Amino acid sequence: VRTIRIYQPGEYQPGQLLELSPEAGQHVGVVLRMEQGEQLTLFNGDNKEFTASIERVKKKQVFVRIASVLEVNRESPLKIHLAQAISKGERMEMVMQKSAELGVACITPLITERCQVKIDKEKMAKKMHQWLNIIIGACEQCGRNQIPELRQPVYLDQFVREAKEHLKLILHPAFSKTWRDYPVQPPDVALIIGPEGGFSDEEIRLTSGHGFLPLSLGPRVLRTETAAITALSVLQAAGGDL
Amino acid sequence: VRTIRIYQPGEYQPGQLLELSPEAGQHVGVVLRMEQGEQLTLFNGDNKEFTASIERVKKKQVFVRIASVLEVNRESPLKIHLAQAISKGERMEMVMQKSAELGVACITPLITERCQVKIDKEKMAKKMHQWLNIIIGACEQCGRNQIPELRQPVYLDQFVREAKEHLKLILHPAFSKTWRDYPVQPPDVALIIGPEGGFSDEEIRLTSGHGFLPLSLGPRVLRTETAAITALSVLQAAGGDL
Ligand SMILES: C[S@@+](CC[C@H](N)C(=O)[O-])C[C@H]1O[C@@H](n2cnc3c(N)ncnc32)[C@H](O)[C@@H]1O
Ligand SMILES: C[S@@+](CC[C@H](N)C(=O)[O-])C[C@H]1O[C@@H](n2cnc3c(N)ncnc32)[C@H](O)[C@@H]1O
Image (cartoon, rainbow over all chains, first blue to last red; front, side, top):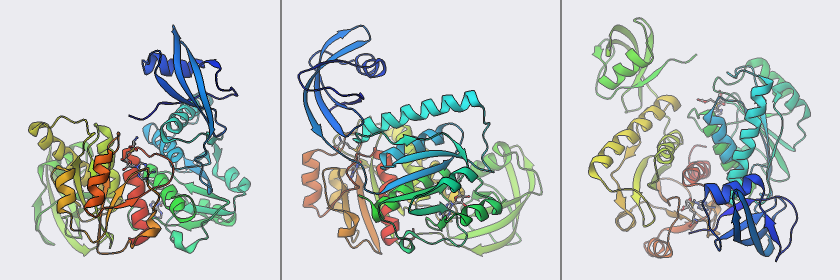
């Protein structure tokens, strides 16, 4: 059995008793049901890991004894900024979880013409909150000791205007080329993946106007959430740490 | 936009009047509520797309008239054999779907040491039916006109003994070799992926001894079902049609 990893930002040092955050301590003592003397690895989002053991469980609060600090970085050298068309429900959560597993540096939810979602300020905020916790959960899972940035949703126009990454790719069949036709390598990539219905010709004219080049992923139509993970897999395997 | 795709095995020809299989009629007649006169693209599993029109719908009996046949092959030239350790519930469903979207040729459900599944012949024949249907659904969605082969569950020990693919790979986070260290090319490749708990040292011992060579997918630990998506994406990108 592997050791449990818990996100706990902030600075602290070995030998120090730490009171776990509300969510951290509620994860450990309540959800995981762990007891005094059990072991834990904490990470702070800054690429450090802290070995620890549970000493006192008082209600939902959890106190942990730090054993040692170690600098452990599992980031890819290829920084990909995913711009993912918003899908309803579980598929978007799937993308949030697995794109973090695949080293994604930064995620922008994208509102595009053929997205089928209701854009409510209250609703969007809840989604953003839920998405960030899924990301942190995936980072506890996969070993990343730095949380990827989850940026506020923007329309296609804004994102394509502000995009400054050195390689800029959109998943779209027309005039597309495979990963071998592009210079996939650090520093960074902007990657647009669209909604189930795809993109309008006007949207392609706008993205193509701002330097986004068309990338294919084989002759089979991939689902929207499949396409994110496949695209990240292929780009990391080409010019990252896969 | 594009016509609804329905898997319909068997032999049939342009100009025939054809009664759809019960599951196909259920899908067309009840789920999708399709009307007489609407169009279907049937595929029989032999890289043929039949254009047909719905001539009568009576609950879940559906009769179509075949108009034309077109040979259309969306199979990867790399034949990948995924042997996926069996995981709980919806994780394995994701593997079946994504791997068919990704062009997998053959799937073997795999029983490894740390799998936590009750070996029940009633459960397992049922589960094999549910996995098959997820696969078939995936070919309908993604455009494969040929169903991947779904084999019976076998234990790791037997699978590794019997494997005959020209390139054999075992996926484990504590490896360092990447896809670039191997001749990933036709005809075929066998790939072994572990459960949520991974492989034991004994299993790594066993598979290495039977010629499965070590493959890593970067320094982050992927969920069992993420690893199937990433591994197939990378292998199709390297030697298939991605
Ligand atoms: C990834 S798809 C999202 C929709 C997905 N089919 C679903 O069910 O949710 C978004 C757009 O990406 C494009 N796309 C999908 N697979 C592709 C591929 N293999 N090569 C190039 N573009 C692709 C398609 O044009 C699609 O309209
Ligand atoms: C959740 S992982 C198993 C974790 C477990 N603690 C272990 O490593 O022994 C499930 C499967 O995904 C595959 N996998 C996950 N990350 C991988 C990586 N970075 N490189 C190669 N295989 C990986 C392995 O085949 C593993 O058995």
